[PDB]
Image 1 (spheres, rainbow, N blue to C red):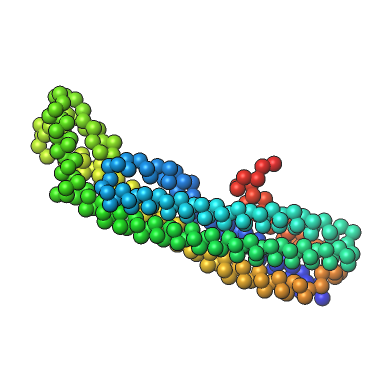
Image 2: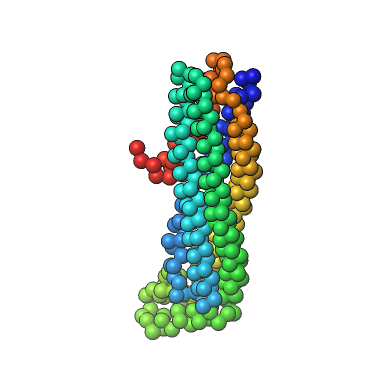
Length: 292
């Protein structure tokens, strides 16, 4: 009757492991969290130079990115705790094979069920955080679209904004000395001969270039936020399936007798299945700050 018991336990461990791996090898990897962290820290740059409307957008975008990041870490710390429970519990599971008996088999059953049970609990808590993270990415992406529209309007050659900058640069250059340099918006530095229009219509292309690069930046962020959103959505969807499968597996395990006459292969296969999740959990915790 062993091979059914073996099936159940292997499936239990591998299923739990696969859910953990949706964080460990998917979420932690395919979303550029680090890039987002750098971006958040930079977004206040040049805040006073944006139009009133653009400024509000950029600000709101920053907050929403901070929230998305905060929520992914909230998810991470919940799953971390499960990982820590799983790694110690599965090591005990492995050791209980030593000088096996019916008591130890019963102990193994309690251990597996706890790992599954704690898993369902923690992963479900984590889902709520992932959903919020998702909704903040989504709201951010919408605002990034509005911002792109706002900037096209602002940076348009015939706009009040753009003209207000062209003449500011001109005034400073006429009030300055020849063969100097003039500072513009968003960091721009220009040579006196470009600004004063010694060669007419050659200052504007410099301003256009700067403003376009600002817009290109927000477009790159938009593309990256949109992709992050699909990826987080795909993971949390897949997690809903896996959480439910863990639930069915827990119920089956509860009605499963662990004490049987396992052959050598079966023992090895069971130990290996447990070891693999232990490794996954250790790699996860180490990435998220677990110190030796």
